[PDB]
Image (spheres, rainbow, N blue to C red):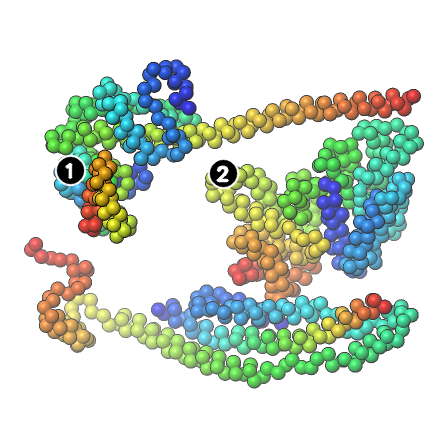
């Protein structure tokens, strides 16, 4: 039983760290969508330009 | 290997990986590739041209074109003419790769010419000094002494096999002249293994002074494992020992791993990890369908976790104890998920 | 960089080995990895910022439409506004999470020291032979309750007595 | 010692007490028992090796305590309990089939076997 | 198959024969029924001895044909130690034991034989494949010689033509 408990002690704090980190990364990844629109616009521009 | 089994495709893949090296400022890594289209229809070369434009490989490419309709004297002199261009790069100390495709039809053109000059036929109704011709061409691919400049010309002639008959006069001659052969195995091609090669019938006698040191370490094992997979193949074609079955799994995962849909080249720093995993048989657990998925995922994992490791592997060029240490940990973690 | 995130992630995967209630928790982690790799391949894929109207307008004889799209890119320089907006929702999650975390942590810390104490109590007190049956009744009136009901029932065999205190009987 | 064996599986090739049903009724064998041959009647068998008890249903056979105290039990196939009501119903069908005369005798053995099984 | 070989040597001696067994691996149902027919049809208890022949699979690379004698009820009767295998008059053990060991011995014999047979089949068919390989190679050399000869006559033809 002591063995089981000791796992839980260390877990309880450390899990809270990953919880925060994971959602934080996702938030940054949102901003990457604005990046995507810059990327997109350029790709399209080169294509139209190529046709000319 | 066998006729148009994407013979040109195997060659073209090298050129595409060479686009990466070419970008590199080291001018020995600037291999100015030359494809020598000998008796190839303008449509076929059109496909090649567009593929080259698509992978932006046009900007070091040279395509000496002797097309299917074009005269047999032009076809005859076409690799020779091409070779002189190659000498210019080589002599300038640069490196370059010339791919003669296909000397078998080059042979036919010389035959046509010789017969038209009433110059006698010889064995397999090919001229006897066809040997002399081929040897002349192939002696222009050479790694020049440093007094004569570091540079070189590298060549990879493509020979089209009439049902895998390497006994044929033009194949026998070339095999002796060249050092190495790659013998693409058509059964494997038909059995949908692309690239299709039997490495029982591929050899290189330019060895590990042409192999990356890192890649050498993790591929002595690879050669041996696949050899066993082949030999112990027939022990599966029967209810037989667990030991054979262990070999077979390890072999099957490896066999699956060396597949690769054509026109996707790979960086050596990503060749090495995939081979490391397979060598360590950590893909044995990974079911065949998930093998494909694993590769790219492992690579992306390596980039997220430590693209420093990839870069480090690249720059050291040798897998240090520290790199194998970090790698063993990393492979396990990815494999676990 | 990403490696800080990932070091906790795989650590949590091997901790999840020790405790598994996960259903879609790993799928959420998988998702966070997915988008992290997606932005990275996005950001590595990233096109040139603007039209190379240095070379390719001076290539073109059909000018002033390279200048049109040059000006259109610079017009559309707002390519899309902020996608940082989470600062309420990230906190909502963090509060609930923190609550759960602290509650659990405090409970298990209590239990750990309690277990140390429990181990010590069995170790420093334990009768080996002598022990009055009255001391057991004193430790459990459950004893007398069971005895009185069993006598009332007319079961003078106790279930399980036989199966670990084998019969000694004349028969 | 027991040497319960079948041309199918080797069951219990010391097995302290074995209780057997023989044409001599029921016979029990314990440690050193006198060396006999007994034709085993189709049976519900208990095999005990120490205190643990395992419950064979046995197709009849031969039993032979050998003088080296090896109880060679030879039977075609044999615990029975995992196999176990539709077999009793189809056995009633076989009993009605005993109207049809060797076939009657076969069906009768089937009825005997159901009764023997049904007891456990 | 064994029917055919013996049937040639003595056909009168074949009195009862059994077919439709070989397909399956040995099974009690078969042994029991064959035994039952052997008792009823041939009244084999009155035959001075029984002998059964089978193939003892000496090694999984060999088979030595072997035989053993099925002890009849008279043998059981007249065996001296049988009182140290005490049994009553009632439920006469020879009359059950004969029949019981008729099947048990036969089934075991059958198992040994079939095990040798399938083992031999693997071995033989492997050796057949090897023998076939040798023949492949022998006809290959002939093919190559013949192919070469065609070339020679063709070359002569070209030269003969060119000379004119």
Q: Quadrant of the N terminus of chain A?
A: bottom left
Q: Residue B273: image x %, image y %?
A: 62, 56
Query: Tag 1, which chain?
Result: D
**For residue A52, what is the image quadrant?**
bottom right
Of E46 and C165, nearer the camera is E46
* Residue at point 86%, 46% (across, down): B67
Disc on res. E137: none
* Residue at point 41%, 26% (across, down): E63
Task: Tell me if B13 is positioned left or right of B286 in this view.
Answer: right
Asked whether residue B87 is in view, the answer is: no
Q: Which residue is mark 2?
A: B238
**For residue B141, what is the image quadrant?**
top right
* Furthest-front residue in this view: D99
Q: Is residue E140 above or below residue D43?
A: above
Disc on res. D23: 1
Q: Residue C151: image x %, image y %?
A: 10, 71
Characterize the local packing of mark 1: few (<14), some (14-19) or many (20 or more) Cα atoms within 10 angstroms.
some
Kindly state the secondary structure of the residue where label 2 is placed: loop
Characterize the local packing of mark 2: few (<14), some (14-19) or many (20 or more) Cα atoms within 10 angstroms.
few
Asked whether residue C106 is in view, the answer is: yes
Q: Residue B225: image x %, image y %?
A: 58, 45
Kindly state the secondary structure of the residue where label 1 is placed: loop
Say yes or no: labels 1 and 2 on the same chain: no
Q: Is residue A34 above or below residue E43?
A: below
**Front label number (1 vs 2):** 1
């Amino acid at each position: 039983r002591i063995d089981s408990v000791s796992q839980l002690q260390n877990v309880a704090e450390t899990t809270k760290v990953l919880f925060d980190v994971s959602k934080e990364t996702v938030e940054l990844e949102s901003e990457a969508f604005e990046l995507k629109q810059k990327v997109e616009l350029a790709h399209e521009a080169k294509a139209v330009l190529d046709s000319w | 290997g066998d006729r148009q089994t994407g013979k040109t495709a195997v060659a073209l893949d090298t050129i595409l990986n060479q686009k990466r090296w070419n970008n590199g400022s080291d001018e020995s890594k600037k291999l100015y590739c030359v494809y020598v289209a000998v008796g190839q229809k303008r449509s076929t070369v059109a496909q090649l041209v567009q593929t080259l434009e698509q992978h932006d490989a046009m900007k070091y490419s040279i395509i000496v074109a002797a097309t299917a309709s074009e005269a047999a004297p032009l076809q005859y002199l076409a690799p020779f003419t091409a070779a002189s261009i190659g000498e210019w790069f080589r002599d300038n100390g640069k490196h370059a790769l010339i791919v003669y495709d296909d000397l078998s039809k080059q042979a036919v053109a010389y035959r046509q010419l010789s017969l038209l000059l009433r110059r006698p036929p010889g064995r397999e109704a090919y001229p006897g000094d066809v040997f002399y011709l081929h040897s002349r061409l192939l002696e222009r691919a050479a790694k020049l002494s440093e007094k004569e400049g570091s540079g070189s010309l590298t060549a990879l002639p493509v020979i089209e096999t009439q049902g895998g008959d390497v006994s044929a006069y033009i194949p026998t001659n070339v095999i002796s002249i060249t050092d190495g052969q790659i013998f693409l195995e058509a059964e494997l091609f038909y059995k949908g293994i692309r690239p299709a090669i039997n490495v029982g019938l591929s050899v290189s006698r330019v060895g590990s002074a042409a192999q990356v040191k890192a890649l050498k370490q993790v591929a002595g094992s690879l050669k041996l494992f696949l050899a066993q997979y082949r030999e112990v193949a027939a022990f599966a074609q029967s209810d037989l020992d667990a030991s054979t079955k262990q070999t077979l799994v390890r072999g099957e995962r490896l066999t699956q791993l060396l597949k690769q849909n054509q026109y996707s080249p790979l960086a050596t720093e990503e060749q090495v990890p995939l081979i490391y995993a397979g060598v360590n048989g950590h893909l044995d657990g990974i079911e065949l369908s998930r093998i494909g998925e694993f590769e790219s995922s492992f690579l992306s994992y390596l980039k997220s976790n430590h693209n420093e490791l990839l870069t480090e592997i690249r720059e050291k060029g040798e897998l240090s104890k520290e790199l194998l240490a970090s790698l063993k940990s990393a492979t396990e973690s990815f494999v676990a998920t | 960089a990403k490696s800080a995130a990932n070091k906790l992630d795989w650590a949590k995967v091997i901790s999840s080995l020790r405790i598994t209630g996960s259903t879609a928790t790993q799928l959420s982690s998988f998702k966070k990895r997915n988008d992290e790799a997606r932005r990275q391949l996005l950001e590595l894929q990233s096109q040139p910022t603007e039209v190379d109207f240095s070379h390719y307008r001076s290539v073109l004889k059909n000018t002033s439409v390279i200048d049109k799209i040059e000006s259109y890119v610079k017009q559309y320089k707002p390519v899309k506004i902020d996608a940082s907006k989470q600062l309420q929702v990230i906190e909502s999650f963090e509060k609930h999470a923190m609550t759960n975390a602290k509650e659990t942590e405090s409970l298990v810390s209590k239990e750990l020291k309690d277990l140390q104490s429990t181990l010590d109590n069995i170790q420093s007190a334990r009768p080996f032979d002598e022990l009055t049956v009255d001391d057991l009744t004193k430790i459990k009136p459950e004893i007398d309750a069971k005895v009185e009901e069993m006598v009332k029932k007319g079961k003078w065999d106790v279930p399980g007595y036989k199966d670990r205190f084998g019969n000694l009987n004349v028969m | 010692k027991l040497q319960f064996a079948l041309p199918h599986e080797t069951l219990y090739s010391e097995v302290t007490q074995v209780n057997l049903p023989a044409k001599s009724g029921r016979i029990g064998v314990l440690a050193n028992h006198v060396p006999t041959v007994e034709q085993l009647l189709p049976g519900v068998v208990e095999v005990m090796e120490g205190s643990n008890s395992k419950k064979f249903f046995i197709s009849g056979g031969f039993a032979t305590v050998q003088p080296d105290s090896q109880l060679c039990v030879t039977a075609i196939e044999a615990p029975l309990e995992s196999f176990s009501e539709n077999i009793k119903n189809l056995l009633a069908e076989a009993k009605k089939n005993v109207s049809s005369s060797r076939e009657a005798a076969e069906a009768a053995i089937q009825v005997e076997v159901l009764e023997n099984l049904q007891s456990v | 198959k064994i029917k055919m070989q013996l049937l040639r040597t003595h056909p009168n001696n074949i009195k009862l024969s059994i077919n439709g067994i070989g397909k399956d691996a040995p099974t009690f149902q078969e042994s029991a029924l064959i035994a039952d027919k052997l008792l009823s049809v041939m009244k084999a208890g009155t035959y001075p001895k029984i002998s059964i022949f089978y193939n003892d699979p000496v090694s999984s690379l060999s088979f030595e044909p072997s035989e053993k004698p099925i002890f009849n009820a008279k043998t059981i009767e007249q065996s001296p130690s049988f009182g140290k295998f005490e049994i009553d008059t009632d439920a006469n053990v020879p009359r059950d034991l004969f029949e019981y060991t008729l099947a048990n011995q036969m089934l075991t014999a059958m198992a040994q034989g079939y095990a040798a047979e399938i083992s031999a089949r693997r071995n033989a068919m492997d050796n057949a494949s090897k023998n076939a390989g040798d023949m492949i190679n022998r006809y290959s050399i002939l093919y190559n010689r013949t192919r070469q000869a065609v070339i020679t006559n063709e070359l002569v033809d070209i030269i003969t033509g060119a000379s004119s």
